């Protein structure tokens, strides 16, 4: 007899995006920075500019106060290296787990299993707005279909994760995002799925979405021309020059941009934060020799290095382990110096 | 200044689930069949019953008339074999493409690229309701987060596709589905992602969803205890006894049900649909010898064998190629006879 | 604890779009509604001298009888089309003095089950058939939300005596696509109806509900085609002297001095047999002069009188109606008298 | 559809405002208690006089809070004789057209910023209740009450809407006591009918806290009463009170009523409010057993103005000033003290 909502415990009140947009409207200056940075990134994706996009910051945001502090330091390096590097902070609020775990600040901002999503969204949007108001553009992984309506207007670059690059509904979502999007290769190293994803996301789609007012609707997208691939390792790493060369060839064969991003962390560092510097060194070497197909890198970085299970220590990750502020200074100096040369020989 | 909905061509009106439910309420008999079949499948997932679940029918539904016809012939065999087999039809609307493609009857029911989703959802619900009214239970792939509200009440068994088994939001969805759910191994043969998915989908989750009235809300699920894995091939086929045994070991090590399903089609039968008979023969041999870990199989079958690009011929697939009615009779007789013996052993 | 505590339940309501999807307006219904709205406008502003006749049941409680009534009425609408513009009364919302059955929408099964989803569906289906067969429809707009479900099928709307003075009803009218008549107050006050025309002709902002069933701010453009309806008070107000006083008051307010006269309710003192007398008096005014009259309203059904329970087919369960025979008589009388008025131009 | 609709715009639902401005425990307690205390006056268990007093309309929250702070001293001073509740009327009905109030147009310049107005209304009501001043308002619209009814201790249905079935339905579901005014020409029967209608359960179309239309089923409002507010001639005197009470008993509803000192009872003249209150004082001294409350249009400064030039001066109906408010309240308190003394 019963066949409906058999395994639904309850359905709860959700404020629609407009309620958050009314409290936290985007400022003139945030609008300008987002607009500009999106353009600048587009220029890197299509080879019109040879600066290196650097998506850098925490694995996950679990404390907005630390995040603003981190941002203030990073901003000095963003300005310092602005002729060599386009620095954008990692501000990831949605985290895909292997089985189960804390899904992030949006899903559970009090870090205690209370799932205060209304608070989380409000907090996320507030942090993003403060970041952009101080001059730091922001990047995030879009994991969910609905959460983007709450803050995509504040995002200069989006990632689609390794676990969702093959998913049609994530490709559809990307096709309708106002920012450039990077698609990671699959968790075991499959690169073709990310190339296919760029293909798919560049076309118009019809999918089911939610309006700013919180109502489901049919969303007809125009396609996203600013997508690229991210090499993030597999069973084996894929950062080096031969993998970059292979990837580029495959990209040209698919008729899509052959400029790509390399993640220094995750499977490319064998899940070991001490190895991110090695990967960045290898990328620096490629940039010095040639490295024509590189347009960016990704780095997991925080105030304090490593990781912890409970949010005990300020500015230390509770998800993947990060390099510390001192290593970040070093890594960025390395990249800037190497890209200066690449840019010179052109 | 412009930063929002830059790559959105339009937002269109979508009737909510309750409009379709009002025109096509579930009947008492459909309700009784769905309820009973879900139970009967759960019994197979947990080793209470040793009948073989058979998920069988078209790769994709593109013509409801042919679908009802196919269903009428299948129904005779469902009855005939009911002591050995639990036959449920494949009624797949949502089709994930490699890159670009026809996404199904929901997404584009007129078969001309007009994306008439309101009509498609209505048509889908109507067919599901007729199928259940005549005594044929239905199964389908849940690809989207929102479409299930329109007809999950008519679905006795759900699949999460190979391309989405890794996706956290698909695992969340499954954790709240009222039916048993099978998770496919990854497109390159990764089994672990499916085993993880079961783990994830058995727990309670909080995520953003859409109510029957078409408004977004926070859904709190109770977890789905009736999930299992589906072996559907990878880089190599994974149907045989050794792969079954490896999978079962890995399932027991993760603490989840070690009863699984084998897909005779897709990567398991490669570039020849008729090899589905070969796979089924190998499964019959396992069932005769032992085959204690097998609880079901999946088969891509239609009125007429093969495939075509345009819907020229009646009852012939326009997606993956299917075995024809005569082979379906043979394949079902083979499975029934073999499982009769397995069941006889005590 | 201070919220929602006199509320027993909130129940599901299908939005207008669900009904519009099942029962889309046809091209012929579209055309008829659009044209009839125009033709009424013309009567309201004195461009045409045909008489608008809003005629039919006090309330609809049976769609089958309503369709039978409509088939007979359609023959007379056609016969008299040079003298009368006939539009059927299709009233689904009824205002009670205290409490009672509020109509088909509110309680379509007549048994206190308040099946509003079914009632809206039924209402829309009856309206669409009516317009498809060539009979335009009129109704009283009582509620703020219900119009989104079928106003597209309505050629003329009434705001009742009990609500002419209400700001939100004046706001609603300011945004209705049809001409609207405003009745004088239940004790005879005419100034409220003249004020209402003033209010409804202007643009307003108020809170409404979209076709998708969501609250929103609606910004109206104003309704230029409103008029008054004289429906009696403590005393009847249908005669030439009342018409003349009303016209003068309308001109003093700068609004249209063309009005409608209701033959029923306080004009007939709730005696359905007197509607014929009122119509006779209007026939006499039309023959003599009657330059300020643009329409009449009449409570008519298949069978005369009223009943408490819906036992007899085609007989009212609200106010008592004249029967089909008297309706023929009354319509012949009005058509013959207005023929002569039209001849003088 | 929509031939004469120029635009449809982006309304925040009640829950957005409730999240920013949740009701406090103290505002909760005051509202709950004051509704009870008013119920008690409606059904004749307490003989204090309900006094609904304040501006015709609220057009400036600053002056409203100033006014509230002065009124709160007198509320407390007279608490054994009078239950003072401030008039906080946002929504205003016009004869034809005009400024419809702070909700509809809070900038007073025809910008119709309804989202801002609803926010401002709720914020003022929450601040008022938090400082100890309960609030009353006219409910004109079917959707606005979802935004702030939780903060209202007493509600009025206006003379122009007492006869309206949808307003009677709305009342039947309001958590507060409700007064129904007699008709603009003096008809009392419509208000008596209204009490009858509002006391029963109804089914109608409303909007949820989330901003979605739905079917609302109400339980009926047992705490309704009539308000005598004049007609063609005034209706405040002892004979009209006696006649009204008799009509109320014949209908089987509470024969305790409220008298409005303003509007048609003062012949639209704010200087006459004091005379009316004098006549009510005299009835309270003599007997006045059927009176449970009064209404007064009062502000910081007297009279009215077309534009909001002077602070604390009405832009709608003309009000008495603060001095006269002190005098009027002292008169009512003294007279009711005696009524209460007689058993
Ligand atoms: N209606 C689904 C559960 C569901 C609810 C909300 C969603 O957004 C998605 C799925 C079922 O019971 O099977
Ligand atoms: N607002 C998103 C696009 C979007 C639209 C609708 C959705 O449901 C989701 C995302 C952006 O600016 O990128
Ligand atoms: N749809 C109505 C106008 C209307 C719009 C919104 C409302 O809430 C009410 C009425 C018409 O076209 O006449
Ligand atoms: N919230 C109101 C009752 C109400 C409910 C629904 C409505 O649409 C209007 C009013 C109260 O507590 O008094
Ligand atoms: Mn990480
Ligand atoms: Mn297939
Ligand atoms: Mn009537
Ligand atoms: Mn006033």
Image (cartoon, coloured by chain):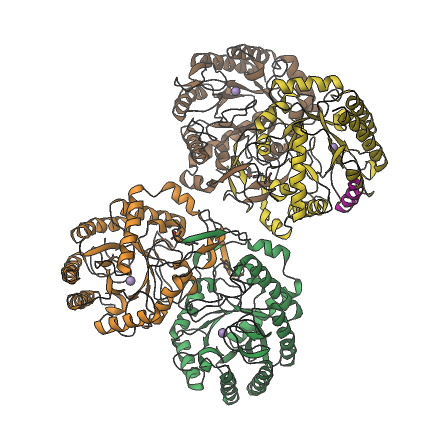
Chain colours: A yellow, B brown, C orange, D green
Q: Is residue A164 visible?
A: no
In the rendered image, the vertical position of residue C124 relative to residue A284, given as above or below? below
Extent of the magenta region: A64-75
Q: Is residue A125 left or right of residue D273?
A: right
Residue C69 location (% of width, % of height): 22, 51
Q: Could you say which quadrant of the image residue C252 lies in?
A: bottom left
Q: Is residue A289 left or right of residue D72?
A: right
Quadrant location, the C terminus of chain B: top right
Residue A331 location (% of width, % of height): 82, 31
Q: Residue at x 64, y 48 (%)?
A: A26
Q: Nearer the viewer, residue B281 or D332?
A: D332
Residue B307 location (% of width, % of height): 46, 15
In the rendered image, the vertical position of residue B105 relative to residue D92, given as above or below? above
Q: Nearer the viewer, residue A305 or D167?
A: A305
Quadrant location, the N terminus of chain B: top right
Which residue lies most toward the right here?
A326
Q: Nearer the viewer, residue A165 or B39?
A: A165
Queried whether the magenta region covers residue A298, the answer comes back as no
Q: Is residue C341 left or right of residue B266?
A: left
């Amino acid at each position: 007899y019963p066949t409906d909502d058999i395994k639904i415990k309850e359905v709860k009140e959700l404020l629609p995006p407009i309620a958050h947009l009314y409290e936290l409207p985007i400022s003139k200056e945030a609008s300008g920075l987002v607009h500009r940075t999106r353009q600048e990134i587009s220029d890197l994706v299509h080879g019109r500019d040879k600066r290196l996009l650097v998506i850098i910051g925490p694995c996950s945001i679990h404390d907005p106060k630390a995040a603003l502090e981190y941002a203030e330091r990073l901003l000095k390096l963003r300005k310092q290296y602005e002729n060599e590097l386009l620095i954008v902070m990692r501000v990831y609020f949605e985290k895909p787990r292997t089985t189960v775990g804390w899904k992030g600040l949006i899903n559970d901002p009090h870090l205690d299993g209370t799932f205060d999503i209304n608070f989380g969204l409000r907090q996320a949007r507030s942090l993003l707005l403060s970041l952009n108001n101080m001059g730091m553009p922001a990047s995030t992984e879009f994991l969910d279909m609905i959460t983007p309506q709450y803050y995509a207007d504040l995002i200069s670059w989006g990632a689609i994760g390794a676990r969702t690059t093959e998913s049609q509904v994530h490709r559809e979502l990307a096709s309708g995002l106002s920012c450039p999007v990077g698609f990671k290769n699959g968790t075991d190293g499959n690169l073709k799925i990310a190339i296919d994803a760029i293909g798919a996301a560049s076309h118009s789609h019809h999918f089911l979405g939610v309006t700013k007012a919180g109502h489901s609707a049919i969303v007809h997208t125009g396609g996203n021309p600013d997508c690229h691939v991210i090499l993030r390792g597999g069973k084996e790493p894929n950062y080096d020059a031969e993998h970059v060369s292979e990837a580029a060839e495959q990209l040209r064969a698919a008729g899509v941009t052959d400029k790509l991003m390399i993640d220094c962390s995750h499977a490319n560092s064998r899940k070991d934060y001490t190895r991110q510097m090695e990967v960045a060194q290898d990328i620096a070497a490629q940039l010095e020799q040639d490295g024509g197909n590189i347009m960016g890198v990704m780095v997991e970085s925080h105030l304090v290095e490593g990781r912890q299970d409970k949010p005990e220590v300020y500015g230390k990750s509770i998800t993947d382990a990060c390099i510390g502020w001192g290593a970040t200074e070093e890594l960025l100096a390395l990249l800037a110096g190497a890209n200066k040369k690449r840019m010179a020989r052109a």
